[PDB]
Image (cartoon, each protein chain N blue to C red):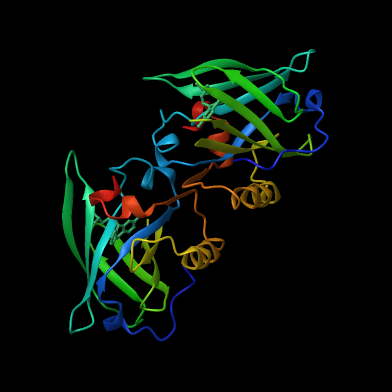
Length: 158
Length: 158
Ligand SMILES: CN(C)CCCN1c2ccccc2Sc2ccc(Cl)cc21
Ligand SMILES: CN(C)CCCN1c2ccccc2Sc2ccc(Cl)cc21
């Protein structure tokens, strides 16, 4: 369903600070409410020395903006990670230059699909957004969002 | 702010049945909740004989999906209509071929801006969506939505 992975991914090199500039999802209800399931705001990507990928992120739960840490285990494919939860959830890195931008998707085999355009600073990278839009033409997305520099510096983008 | 109007608009010819295929807005909160302010689902456009434009639409209010009728008065500019309410609200027709598609925007001078891609049938017109996307490149939109043929036939797109 996501036929776009980064060739030659060096995962150690995605470590550190990231900003969820834009999001997009297969279904409107995955992103429309602040508490919508795919509305996760990346804080930080932390590769483990064994090539697993730890994602630190914020999520609006009930009232507060909550901190969450989730581990995405490595696979044979360098650009694909698994969170064995209620379903097979895969994290796929589509593309990155390591230092400005990183596109990735999360897909639950059930059909549910959300992708993000991550950037290193709180700025609108119009180039990174072009690349994001190009990889989404291929996908059955029905909601897209984008954040301004002010919202990027707030918790949960409020 | 919207520098894209249809040249040579014949307003009588937009009359009758329409479907809100896609929406997009300047701010996420204009479209994110089902009760979000710019989340209006067009039923029908009815030109009056004096060249005023009556919009019949559905809006999710409190619980139910409500019917609403609003009149947009004519101006010197054939493609621009006004709803004199709490602010100057203008309805602008950007483009149409009358028989498949119509792009229009609603703007409140305050900054608040929502645009829609209307189509005549419940079908995904990939061409009409391309034209919609081309007119939005020019605008400071931060949320976009799109509906499937099943949702187009439900009240309020549920
Ligand atoms: C509770 N939330 C931290 C995890 C669920 C949200 N989500 C997600 C987000 C960040 C990292 C991995 C995932 S797995 C996934 C697969 C499909 C969809 Cl649609 C969303 C997600
Ligand atoms: C109560 N709702 C029927 C009218 C308000 C929603 N809305 C709108 C929708 C359909 C026809 C005209 C308008 S004026 C307008 C201007 C700016 C924005 Cl952002 C939204 C709107």
